[PDB]
Amino acid sequence: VLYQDVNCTDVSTAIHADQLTPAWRIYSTGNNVFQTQAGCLIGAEHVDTSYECDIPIGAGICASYHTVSQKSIVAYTMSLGADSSIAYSNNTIA
Amino acid sequence: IPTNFSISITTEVMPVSMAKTSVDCNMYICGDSTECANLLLQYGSFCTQLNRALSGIAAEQDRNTREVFAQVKQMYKTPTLKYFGGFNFSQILPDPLKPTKRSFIEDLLFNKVTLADAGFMKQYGECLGDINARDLICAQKFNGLTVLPPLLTDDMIAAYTAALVSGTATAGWTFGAGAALQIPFAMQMAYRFNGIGVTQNVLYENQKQIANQFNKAISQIQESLTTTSTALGKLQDVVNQNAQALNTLVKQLSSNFGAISSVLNDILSRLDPPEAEVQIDRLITGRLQSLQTYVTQQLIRAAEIRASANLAATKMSECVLGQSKRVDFCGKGYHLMSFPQAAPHGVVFLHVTYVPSQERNFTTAPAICHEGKAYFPREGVFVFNGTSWFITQRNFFSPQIITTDNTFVSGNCDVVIGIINNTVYDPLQPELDSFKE
Amino acid sequence: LVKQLSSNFGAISSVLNDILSRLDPPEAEVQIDRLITGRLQSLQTYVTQQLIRAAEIRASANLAATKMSECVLGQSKRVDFCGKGYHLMSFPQAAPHGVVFLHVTYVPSQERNFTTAPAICHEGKAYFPREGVFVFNGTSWFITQRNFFSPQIITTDNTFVSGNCDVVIGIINNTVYDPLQPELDSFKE
């Protein structure tokens, strides 16, 4: 799930106290990832790695479906691009 | 024919993105009243359509921003020298010692248009902040108007701009065709001149002068962006239009559309439900009309911003990723170079244009008949003549002698009008005369 | 647009022929006027959305027609307009309510490091390359082109005359070749 704009401190309380309106019967909460363009990423792990943006969430954070250890949804820094090794030289021609 | 050159640099501000707004019609109209929501549900799924339209606008803005900025495959590292062939590339690449990861020009751009109408942020709610500072102040309002942060952060935009500048300065211009071919900057400028029409002599023999002119133009751009007025008018006008639209929506929210009061939870407390529904229906209709007008205006503005973003992406792909011979497309005169710069919800290009210099009157010669055959000029198009003396090029003086390598054979002399009788030179005859005799 | 037709715009029922058999004509007037106004507003919103989508499709069609006229009907030197790199060809294909082009682009291949030479002063005059822009040199050896290797020897036909050698920074001393002198020395001498 991805709440539009929340603090990830009141949503958890409303879920644990049955105060949220879209309260599903088989819904739970295992982890919260508070960041810009919030939503707490309930059901996804915030991995410190970087992969190509598959599902654009917002604020530089995206989501995909990779294998942590198994297949699950993660969150990365959008991997803005692959690194290069092009160095300037005044006597090198390619 | 011009006798000198003048390396000028022009600026062009083009918006590529707008304010990603999100208005919850369930909170804007019928904030917390249950009977109000029950009456609103009778009018149909207008709120769902408006939310879908706003989400589509946000997705279109994100896609336009990505297509404009994210155009290269690899992220080329910014060089540490920043001084290639005499051209001082400072204040363009991110400084490795400055706290911010932007350049001086990018800092000047972000410190002159980011006012965002200071004083109107209290109207709508926004979940601003950053996860790095661990503050992340998440503010909300009763009107339901929210502003979603963009996908590409300012840091990623600055990184894309730095990668573009590195791929333009270093590796020449072949980085846009899906490759990476190393080449010095002086040879790149010589090839740009050759593509324009100017020979490499003006570049190599006057490299120091061109570098000094480029540095002076960079300094003039810095001065014009430091303390001036009426700068970055496009982005400022876009922000002002967005703020005015939000303010008009907020004012239309607190409008008494022929009812007892314009504020909710005030007519449900002093009136009876059968007598209050009549007043609720008028307010609901008025707010629905106002929100529909706002959504239509937002769609029109989003289409305009998408067109501007497509134009800016085309300009970038034509001027930064290569050398376009399009007249008055990149800059004022000859393009000859292009450097993009990051800007809030827009792109500011730095077209290093080529402008001629002081001129001089000369004499023309359509053709020259040496021994009965006319000799029309080669690639060097202008036959500069004191009195039928030499043959030169167009964009520069370049005094060069007339030989058989600069002219080709043609018909007689009575076919071209205005032909001037003169003599042609050929290095073969004196060489053979010196070798034999 | 279909689902909005069955919506109670402040009336008793969103289905015709039902409010006329249970209400009075004077009340049925307003009961029908409310539904008429609601349906007119919904249809106006639909027409506005259709106009916006039609303007977008018209812009896309103009862009596609420009791309076709620039890539299929000729050879455009536009950078990253037809395909990825150099255009070099274009083939259009029919598609439902759209056009699918086949840009046969030109992409470079594996590279190799070489040495540069801004100018070559043979006997006091610097020979700048005329056509072949890249002076491929093992150690000041040859002159080639940019988009391909094409190993070609440096001659006087691929270079022109210029000033002295103390004007260009980075000039490498080398020798130029002219086919006239060996031919003359072989024929006469």
Image (cartoon, rainbow, N blue to C red):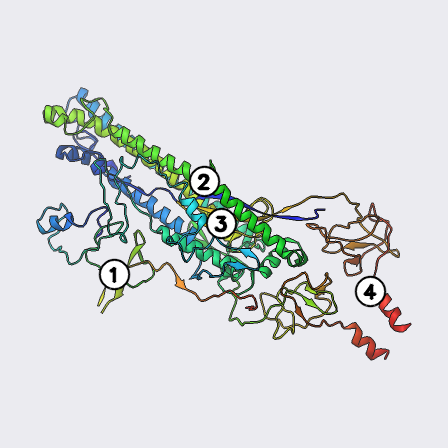
The amino acid beneath tag 1 is: Val
According to the picture, the residue beneath numbered tag 3 turns out to be: B314
**What's the CA distance linking mark 2 and mark 1?**
39 Å
Q: Residues within 10 Å of mark 4 (few under 14, many from 20)?
A: few
Q: Quadrant of residue B361?
A: top right
Q: In the rendered view of the protein, which quadrant contains the C terminus of chain B?
A: bottom right
- Out of A63 and B53, give the one closest to the viewer: A63
**What's the CA distance linking mark 3 and mark 4?**
49 Å
Output the chain of dot 4. Answer: B
Q: Residue A74 shows which numbered tag?
A: 1
**What's the CA distance linking mark 3 and mark 2?**
20 Å
Q: Nearer the viewer, mark 1 or mark 4?
A: 4
Q: Residue B395 at x, y = what percent? A: 68, 50
Label 2: element kind: loop
Q: Residue C176 at x, y = what percent? A: 72, 71
**Considering only order in the chain, which callout, 2 or 3, is on the residue closer to the N terminus?**
2
Label 3: element kind: helix
The amino acid beneath tag 3 is: Thr
Q: Residue B232 shows which numbered tag?
A: 2
Label 1: element kind: strand
Label 4: element kind: loop
